[PDB]
Amino acid sequence: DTALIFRLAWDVKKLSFDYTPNWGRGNPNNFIDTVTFPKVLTDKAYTYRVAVSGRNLGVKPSYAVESDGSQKVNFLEYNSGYGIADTNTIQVFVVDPDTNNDFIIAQWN
Amino acid sequence: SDTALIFRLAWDVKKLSFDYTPNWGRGNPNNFIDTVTFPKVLTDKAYTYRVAVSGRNLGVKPSYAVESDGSQKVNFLEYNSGYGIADTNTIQVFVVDPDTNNDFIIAQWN
Image 1 (cartoon, rainbow over the protein chains, first blue to last red):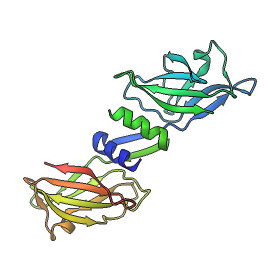
Image 2 (image 1 turned 180 degrees about the horizontal axis):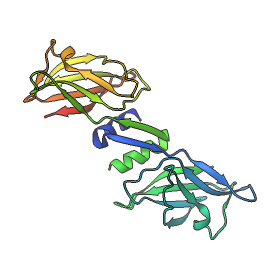
Image 3 (image 1 turned 90 degrees about the vertical axis):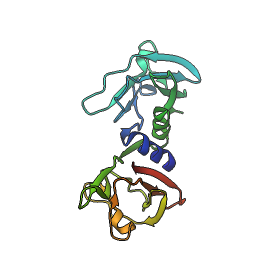
Image 4 (image 1 turned 45 degrees about the horizontal axis):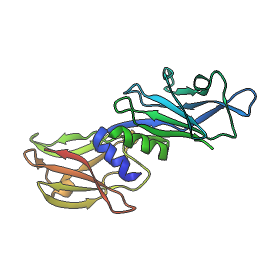
C-alpha cells in the first residue's frame, strides 16, 4: 500500500477519499437496503455495479453526491424496490467511465 | 491507470488524505532553489528524504518535523553543504519508507 500511495502521490499529487462501507439495513432488519461512502471521488461520473451471491445485477445511474460529500448506493434500485437478505454475499464495484473497468469497493459477507 | 490504483488503494485502506504537490522555495538570489515543501504528508511512519542533484546522490536525512498545518519542508542547504541549488540543475526528492528502505520519487525540478 505504501508503494501504491507514493506512486499516486507522484501521479495525482493530491488525493482525499473515504470509502468505508456504511451498510443500511431495511425493514425488516434482516435486509440490507443500502451502502454509503462518506467521501467519494467526484472528478468522474462513476457508476456502481452490484453482484448478489456471484450474480450480476448490473449498473444503475449514480445518486447525486450529498453536501457532506457522501454517496449512497441503493440496492432497491438494483433489486426491484426490495433490499437484499443479509445471508447473501453482496458486492459493489465502482465503474470507471473512461474504461468501463470496475473495482471492488464494498463487500457484505 | 491512476483510477485503478486509487480504487485498489481505497479498497485496502478505506480512508486517506495527502498532498505531495511540490512547493519550491527559492533562495538568495532567487535563481537558486533552496527548499521544497509538501502541504499534507503521511504521518504513519517516520519518513525520511533522499536528495539527488544532476545525478549526484546527496544521501538521506530526516527533514524538519511535520508542521501543525500538516506540511513538511525539505531543506536542500542541509544536503548541499550549506548552499542552495542553481535552478539549471535537476533536483530529485525521494521519500524513504523506514520500514523497507525503499525510495519513491516525490519531487523533481527540471
